[PDB]
Amino acid sequence: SKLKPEVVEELTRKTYFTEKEVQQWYKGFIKDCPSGQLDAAGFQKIYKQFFPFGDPTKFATFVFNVFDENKDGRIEFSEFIQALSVTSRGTLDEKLRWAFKLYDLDNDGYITRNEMLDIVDAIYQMVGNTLPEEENTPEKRVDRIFAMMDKNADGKLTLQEFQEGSKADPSIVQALSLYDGLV
Ligand SMILES: [Ca+2]
Ligand SMILES: [Ca+2]
Ligand SMILES: [Ca+2]
Ligand code: NA
Image (tube, rainbow, N blue to C red; front, side, top):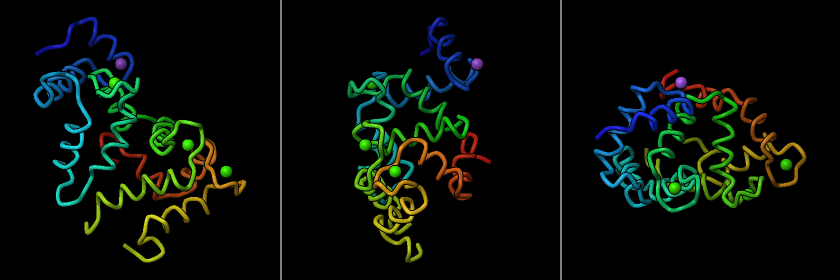
């Protein structure tokens, strides 16, 4: 199955991929999702493929919701390739804007402790028996992040607090500096 020329052209101009790369990703996408419409269950499936033994089910749902840009309940190829482009090849600022969207569950422009607790709980569930005290619970992790990033101590992180606090921490910068998962 191949992408219509005018479609690959558009997706090439909107992502950090070449035309060949867009075509290769379309083929992988379809081999796995012949309908071209990825549902949350088949998304959760794929994360298990990458992260067996743990329980990525909740984290996969949160990630699915960011991929599902128009909030229609399915991931189509245009959403898939754009989310891949930013998460794997975006600049630091673009990656941090995308991560903010992940944590901001209700899309109101802030990340609250509870929202972040929900995501970090979900991450801890995914990894699990795959840590130091001071960071052995999602609660301790969220406390550390808010200590570092919540500059006006109001229990919320704005985009700018999240971006600057992330750029201050070398481990985070290291995680966001990957290109295709390689630095
Ligand atoms: Ca969608
Ligand atoms: Ca929010
Ligand atoms: Ca704040
Ligand atoms: Na291009």
